[PDB]
Image (cartoon, rainbow, N blue to C red; front, side, top):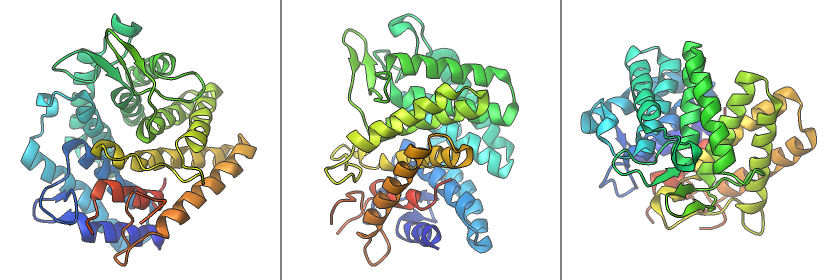
Length: 334
């Protein structure tokens, strides 16, 4: 019910069936940014997986293909002309997931070709002892927002192919990222900048991809340290990226961060599922579940009459698709 309603409302408000892209906001004057569009693509896939309504499920499955078509019409099929390695990797990850759902070989090609471009040419051992560069134009920083998503993309490709190449890549990337882009106790740093060092600013989306990569590695390897890694990062988020009532922060004004709760919620759902499944960390699991439900209820209590929820979950014209996606994601967790 609620996840179905939330997704249908989001589509009614933001989906452009003519361009086959989401609008950036309810003024319907500009389509969504390239990288963010991959994250809305994954929202469609999560709703597809979450729904028990067969009619909605089939509509969402078609929409998975249409989102790709709309983006390819505007941006092409070869994204390696984009100087942002993260942009490429968000799309490689989405493509791997789209392949798992549809079996359409164009998605496996897209995922594998773009993952290889980034991992094979943009990994460097010299600066900071490892890590993938943020950009393929200039090599000045190595960022959480490329490295943890790269580990996740590798995990999906391992799941598809069973090629140990991809598990080995995930393991290597994650080990470097845990060492160089975290404090060892679940705080994920934004980036490490050449001639400066680490920039220890934490954000929702980087907590999220660290958590998802850790959960995926736990499932692929059987090494309990990874589940512990995930739990520590979830605790940090719950205690340190929230307001005084425990509601997740609103990260504006930066446009990229405003919707980051979307990526966080997607990955917190993976941890919740694994904790429920395994029975590990039962004390934390109970606390975590209660805190998640609280956040979701507060967010949805601010829905407008069209069932759209702005990204400021703690409070109150024009609604933006990225900021509004997080509440929809929260009701479509898998």
